Image 1 (cartoon, rainbow over the protein chains, first blue to last red):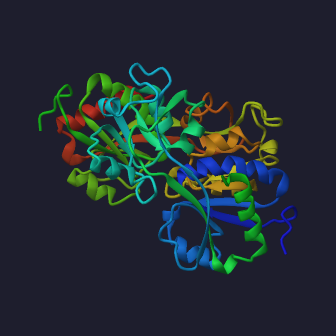
Image 2 (cartoon, rainbow over the protein chains, first blue to last red):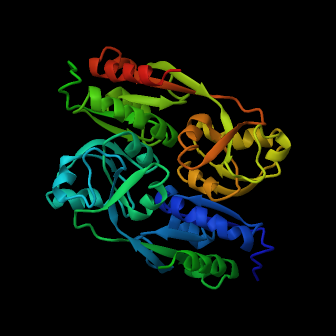
Image 3 (cartoon, chains in turn orange, blue):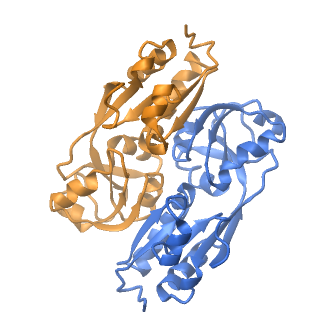
Length: 212
Length: 213
């Protein structure tokens, strides 16, 4: 059985940096009263062999868009968030909602976001004929907040990311002028642990906390 | 090979960590908008590929961080040293400053693995001092540390330059570290084959000017 309160067990959760920045604060909040003695540890999906690890029990849950997890895996879609345009509050030019015209007038900071749901936007936009001035290109999102705060660069980020960054770095978000598809976040677990007490508990909590 | 900042459309490739990226880029991009408007910057992880072979070939112009691996054939410039500190939210009910070594072991922690970096040697340093922290949460990198501390009572061991980028934005505060940890020497790197490369020298000196304490 599983006693969430008395549990000393450790859960290993695979997620991206966007998902980690979004899920972790609220989860650690909820676990404070529900499961004060358990331990959480996170990894990047790409960090190794997600497939083979979730199956052996090394990874308990995976989060994000993971087309590679098909056979042997259940998935419970949590929500969708769309792409927004982020720039600093007191930007001299930027307006909201930003027009597609100004979007290409301004300079950008682009996240490669290689091998995630967000690495797709770069080609989606260059195929749409939308040419940008990437003054800067970084692999991940850790510095997007600070960079937008000190410059006149604009960025295309997941709306969940802006949720965590708007107030802290004094930024404004705009509905994305481009026709960008929604990015779906799913809850993944292996069939082997479909009826494992612990796994059902944690994944039910994720649903309770983050399901739209 | 001539380099003219005002009209150059060149692309420099910079290797740095998540912390370095967060610390260096904002001031850098702010400076370039006024000095090198048309050049492009691209960052990568030092651990993502063959940094040595990349810097020799010229696919990577500069490297920032610890990088004890780069020795012969690499020029090196010190920028600054900074220490580890305890970071907790400003309205934390227990945490004080300076935090005692006793309280440090009674509060619940959020640890960063920081694998294959200097910041990943911390956990072992504390263990060997007999300090067994309550590791309630462990994450691979630093990105979420700010938000996590903002909404919890967890405390974190973090590089001072990182805490600086987080204190005001996330309503946090720091304490000098109760434990004996060394400080962190952040250096600038460039291969020998580009000591006389004007474009490389130029950007190189901008780092010295902007970042050397």
